[PDB]
Picture: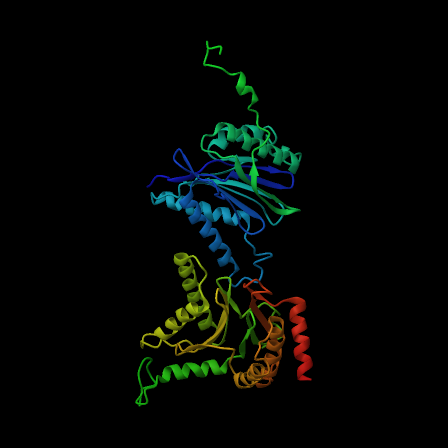
Length: 233
Length: 243
């Protein structure tokens, strides 16, 4: 048992017709102090999987090393390491899910919430969640922390059920993700303007976007707000 | 007499006959070589086709350690696999603690100490393999060869197995004729030739050629197998030289 020290906030994601999108901001908070402003919380594994991690950053870096080591180990005595016997999103997730549940069972958890986003060999979209308790679930949209409360409602308006996935394009899906990231910046006190976004498409492959910013913000109406009730000036 | 019946026993000469008997198992094995080039290393091995029923290109002999080290060996194949498994554990614990990938000289000693430890007790048998290995690190390219005794040195070119004398002679010519150095793509071609020339010692059965390489320019300092057109190009070059 411990407590999280340096922490990362929401990771948000959704499925679309040809793949999956995942995003997370670049902040490493130290309680109320916004300590580290250049933290990458989306970690790609091969060219078909992106693991988005929130919560304790020291445990994130540990998980990052496990995944790095997993790729190395998979390549050993494996002539088809870059083909038929490459790491799948489902393999990577199940491994993490096993570790998370084992660690919680020893009363020494990895203090994280994780979303594994990717595309399988047969082109099927993969999107599944796991956290410090070893709890797992899948959904057309997935989000951690504040994202669960604010991003999911917005993303579910685009893809409300399974049958909405083929009707959703990559442009519409990315637009929804970017809007959600803006809303989180308005309302989450442990978020930053800077974020990373990753698209895993079955046709165009893995597109990893860094140094994105929240833009088109509405603040002008603030000038008209005066006092807390009766004050006019 | 009786000094050769137990491992780790010094004979009146000061010799460990059990290690010398392990060398005989190595000498009985197929030919494997290593060539140090300008910015990397090249490994090649002779695979005897015992039967038509063997699936081509499937029974891979050369093994990778970490992502930057290549390992090949002659003698008892399982013993080599055991040594590579240990090498992988050694490389993982090094990278775990020190972050950086294990340097080749550092890696060489890890294997060396482990093999040497199997000459210290009668409760274990020495390794029945000579292992040629190496790769690229921060200080550049390195090639090593490790014997059953645990003895290893750095090499410009290395060879072991049944056709080692033939191979060694060919490697010595390259060192003399190329003091300024040899390129990676050249080394692959030369490696193919040397294996074909060394095959005269195992001329009864036909064979399959297998090559790998680590090069700073050609492979970004990562270990990769030579495949497809580049492999066929090396085979054609090798076949042309024997005729």
